[PDB]
Amino acid sequence: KVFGRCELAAAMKRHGLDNYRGYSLGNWVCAAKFESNFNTQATNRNTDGSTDYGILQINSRWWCNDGRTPGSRNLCNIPCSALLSSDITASVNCAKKIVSDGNGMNAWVAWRNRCKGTDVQAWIRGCRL
């Protein structure tokens, strides 16, 4: 499913992400924008052999099991294909574990290159929340 901007903002707030570990909504919506372009089915293969999955491009070396990343840790205890669903629940519950890992949203490279220190409030600007 390709989400609309305020449609995803409302789903993420509904699932507890506005100000989760101090990160406003605006940060999370900017992160999904540049990671997957709001498309729950986006996948991208990395040069080390792992793959990134879903709306927030969660990586199979640490976070989910896709059966083709040797040495992977599956810390969110989930098949990576659960991350491609039109229901973002599994993606949001895994992202909550990743932001808590010591480095916050710096774990998402497009958040720190494109979102970090920008006016992220603009991403939730016309929405009924």
Image (cartoon, grey):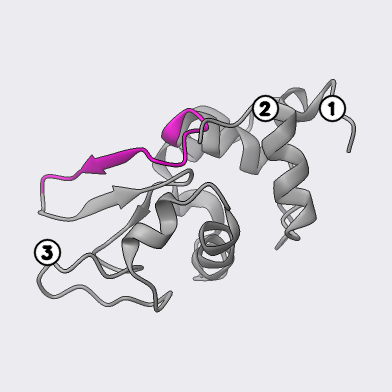
Dominant secondary structure of the residues highlighted in magenta in the image: loop
Q: Amino acid at mark 1?
A: Cys
Q: Is residue 7 visible?
A: yes
Q: Residue furthest right?
A: 128
Disc 2: which residue:
5
Disc 3: which residue:
68
Give neighbour class at mark 1: few <14, some 14-19, many 20+ (Cα, 10 Å).
few
Q: Is residue 19 visible?
A: no
Q: Nearer the viewer, residue 41 or 103?
A: 41
Q: Check whether the beta carbons of the residues at disc 1 and disc 2 lie within 8 A of each other.
A: yes
Distance in Å between CA atoms under marks 2 and 3? 32 Å
Residue 26 is drawn in which quadrant? top right
Q: Amino acid at mark 2?
A: Arg
The location of residue 48, given as percent across then percent down, is 11, 53
Along the horizontal axis of the image, is 112 left or right of 9? Answer: left
Along the horizontal axis of the image, is 45 left or right of 123? Answer: left
